[PDB]
Image 1 (cartoon, chains in turn brown, purple):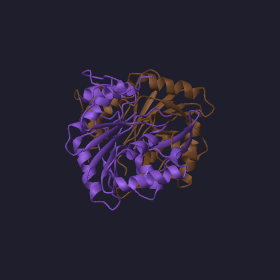
Image 2 (cartoon, helix red, strand yellow):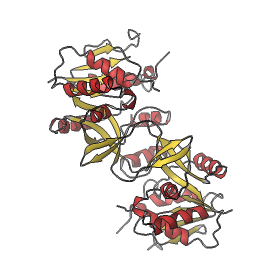
Image 3 (cartoon, one colour):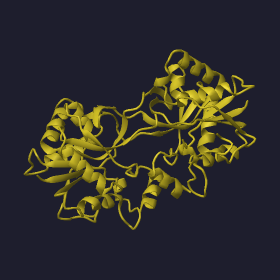
Image 4 (tube, helix red, strand yellow):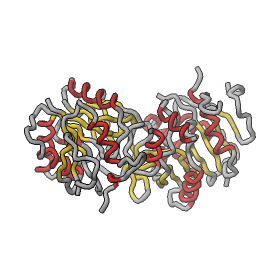
Length: 217
Length: 217
């Protein structure tokens, strides 16, 4: 089957953070697109968001499409733009700002997911710190240990089932409750496997993990 | 009032990970003890666990005491060993393996906590990644966004109320449900404030964050 990557734009929730030339004059989005562009495992990459002058990519593998109100919508759109898509194709949804994901992790994810009952999987890191929930800088609830992970991307699923979960969530107005790809699947009744990546795989939100990203290399 | 620091041993759950000379021949525990040893804000530090030959500290500010079956117990013990303790003293419980916490954060925590209704506070980082819960490497549940933080230490509380929460949790067999200091307080009916630290403040569990720790410096 074919392997597709969807890379969403996100501001949820002028000049998106993803046009940020970080180190080596290398745009934060472009550095991410690299690991999938230069990899024959991925057939097409759907970048959803004036992209003429982004500009680094009017590349063969790259297909641009219309981002939406939310991450969910951008991914939904991207799915809807995959012509000649088949139920058994593969979709990796990935953060525009994670150019630190390792190849070993992506491979582990694909293989393990491919042999799973679910046919869905996410990269994830285990949570050893206590998860709290907070209202107005006050701790309102706490989570009992220990089966807790923070989800990292790529998140991977067979295409057909992913589209059905998305249609299900959209048509039932569960979009706001949707956070990652896995949560859409779970609401649809599909529970993805978890594949441990490295804490080195982080999303670039702050100036601090930007530093981590540079010392990363 | 007096400011006490409790630093627990933890293996939960021969030669504890805390006798690990990391960089500069500087033991992971010792590097942590540094930020509190060399700071006049802290009056005494209780290190709970053959400590003669640990060895770097038979120091003035340092008091050793008997660690327990769990982190809860080690802290409980340490509380019970604070002679001349007063209800309005302060207790910072801190991870033996976080020598990366910044002074600014500790100060922010103390001040904000001191002027709060709770008189308890924790350092914390916001969670932007989706929190999952997992059984047998399979995602069983997911958390709806977005009021989610991972708790980091120090965790800080007035002494009296902390002892009452601990007595309450012990005497009601809630110890296994206890994860951090804040969770003991919450079960006691006290909700701590949250003070945002930096993602740079991490616990040394892996070889990867050990690398982060060295590039940290």
